[PDB]
Image (spheres, coloured by chain):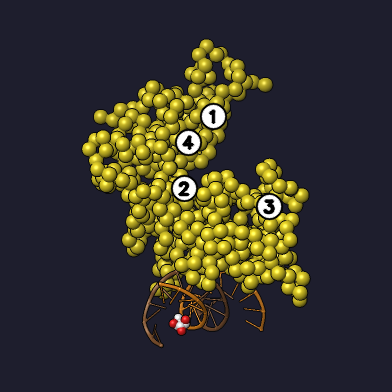
Chain colours: A yellow, B orange, C brown
DNA sequence: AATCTTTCACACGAT
DNA sequence: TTATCGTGTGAAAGA
């Protein structure tokens, strides 16, 4: 039979956190292909296997007699339906692979879709199916000044974008901004997702902060920060490109798949520019005829696109189980009700089932399934964490985790805090 | 008439 | 030479 997670096993997990994680990184919109064309998803969706649990699982499989081909994670990716065969990714030796030739035909009538990633081990032991976030289908980018009512295609401060340069409508020339080897590079094989933070015009340099909310407009100062390494570029002014020129006076919202240039703030007309694998500053030339434009190098024009990340984390808390781990529950948000006679926490998210219980630290809570997107649980008394406490004496923070009946543990990033009364 | 989005069509420059 | 592949850009068709 399947063994329920014990308090001892949960304490062992919480100490180490050797999870297996699957990340799916992708753009938030995709341009459709008409007739027989293939307009590829750019940047190419990327599946990453993170966490120390993949190595531990491989050692367990080999110890049980599996060869390296048998213990290797395999993955296929496809669009939500199809009609298209799924494409095989190759994860051997790397912990990631990009899907470089996905496209969506106009014969597909959906306005939005998710990528589906199917994973199993080389011996055919099933891992399961993992969905991307939603991707909006577009016919082609609009040429008109964007309206903030198309909130949908605008770029909010604090969200993530990919940036890429392509030289002469040539697919082979495409390079993405990507941090690797301690530096910003322009890679043909991997791409970074960069937080784009709006700064007020008065912000100076480093390290340092000041969150400004709102949508990004041309002429605004931004900071781009690698979502993986945290590496930041200097303050940039984002500028509209048309032809081989940057516009100095444009002030409209930046939108999906626009071409933009990044002026290095406070420099003499220096722009972020690609040279082969290198990212450099290159100086624009003024147009003596139009004061509000300057001529920029081809390597200084970048296509911007918003990106998203689906992240799924699982751990065999009671050892290998018969049932595949998916659909992996995801908790988006927690809310303390309070409300009535007993304190309840409401979890909002996805893939919830009645076979999940909420654990607060190493304490299993009474859990009430409402639907795939909603579960309630009863908050443990503080005495479950501090023996003898009759009230919350000092703040106490506990992790919140979901646990399946066979002991599979699904980590959340979220915590619950007990706070003393005023 | 003029505008904006969607679909069709073909040029550009790569292989 | 032409043949063909993604990609960019306009024309055409729809709203
Ligand atoms: O590059 C133009 C060549 O002469 C033809 O092959 C076409 O331009 C390609 O469609």
| Residue at mark 2: chain | A
Q: Which residue is mark 2?
A: A310
Which residue shows up at 44% across the image and 50% down it? A24
Task: List x then y, in percent, for residue A302.
Answer: 59, 63
CA neighbours of label 1 inside 10 A, class few (<14), some (14 to 19), many (20+)? some
> How far is the residue under mark 4 from the one under mark 2?
13 Å
Disc 3 Cβ-to-ligand 1 distance below 8 Å: no
Numbered-mark total? 4
| Residue at mark 4: chain | A
- Of badges 2 and 1, nearer the viewer stands 2
CA neighbours of label 3 inside 10 A, class few (<14), some (14 to 19), many (20+)? many
> How far is the residue under mark 2 from the one under mark 1?
23 Å
- Of badges 4 and 3, nearer the viewer stands 3
Looking at the rendered image, the quarter that the C terminus of chain A falls into is: top right
Q: Which residue is mark 4?
A: A412
Q: Which residue is mark 3?
A: A235
Task: List x then y, in percent, for residue A32.
Answer: 46, 67
Element marked by disc 3: loop
Which residue shows up at 71% across the image and 47% down it? A205
Element marked by disc 2: strand
Can you say whether A363 is above or below A266 in the image?
above
Front-most of B7 and A26?
A: A26
Which of the two discs, 4 and 2, labels the residue nearer the N terminus? 2
In the displayed structure image, the side of residue A340 where residue A204 appears, left or right: right
Q: Which residue is mark 1?
A: A416
């Amino acid at each position: 039979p399947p063994k329920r997670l014990t308090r001892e096993a949960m304490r062992n997990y919480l100490k180490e956190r050797g999870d297996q994680t699957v990340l799916i990184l992708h753009a938030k919109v995709a341009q459709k292909s008409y007739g027989n064309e293939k307009r590829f998803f750019c940047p190419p969706p990327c599946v990453y296997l993170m966490g120390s649990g993949w190595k531990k699982k491989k050692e367990q499989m080999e110890r049980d007699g599996c060869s390296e081909q048998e213990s290797q994670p395999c993955a296929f990716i496809g669009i939500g339906n199809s009609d298209q065969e799924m494409q095989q990714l190759n994860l051997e030796g790397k912990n990631y692979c990009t899907a470089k030739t996905l496209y969506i035909s106009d014969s597909d009538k959906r306005k939005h879709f998710m990528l589906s990633v199917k994973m199993f081990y080389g011996n055919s032991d099933d891992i399961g199916v993992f969905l991307s976030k939603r991707i909006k289908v577009i016919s082609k980018p609009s040429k008109k000044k964007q309206s903030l009512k198309n909130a949908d295609l605008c770029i909010a401060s604090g969200t993530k974008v990919a940036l890429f340069n392509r030289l002469r409508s040539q697919t082979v020339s495409t390079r993405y901004l990507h941090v690797e080897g301690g530096n910003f590079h322009a890679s043909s094989q991997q791409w970074g997702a960069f937080y784009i933070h709006l700064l007020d015009d008065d912000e100076s340099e480093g390290e340092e902060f000041t969150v400004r909310d709102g949508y990004i407009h041309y002429g605004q100062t931004v900071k781009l920060v690698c979502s993986v390494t945290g590496m930041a570029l200097p303050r940039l002014i984002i500028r509209k490109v048309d032809k081989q020129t940057a516009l100095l006076d444009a002030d409209d919202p930046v939108s999906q798949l626009h071409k933009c240039a990044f002026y290095l703030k406070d420099t003499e007309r220096m722009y972020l520019c690609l040279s082969q694998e290198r990212i450099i500053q290159f100086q624009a030339t003024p147009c003596p005829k139009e004061q509000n434009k300057e001529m920029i190098n081809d390597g200084a024009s970048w296509t911007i696109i918003s990106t998203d990340k689906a992240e799924y984390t699982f751990y065999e808390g009671m050892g290998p189980v018969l049932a595949p781990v998916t659909p992996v529950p995801v908790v988006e948000s927690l809310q303390l009700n309070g409300g009535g006679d007993v304190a309840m926490l409401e979890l909002t998210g996805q893939n919830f089932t009645p076979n999940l219980r909420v654990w607060f630290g190493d304490v299993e809570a009474e859990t009430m399934y409402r639907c795939g997107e909603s579960m309630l649980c009863v908050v443990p008394d503080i005495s479950a964490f501090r023996e003898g406490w009759r009230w919350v004496r000092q703040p106490v923070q506990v992790p919140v985790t979901l646990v399946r009946n066979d002991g599979v543990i699904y980590s959340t990033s979220l915590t619950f805090t007990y706070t003393p009364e005023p």
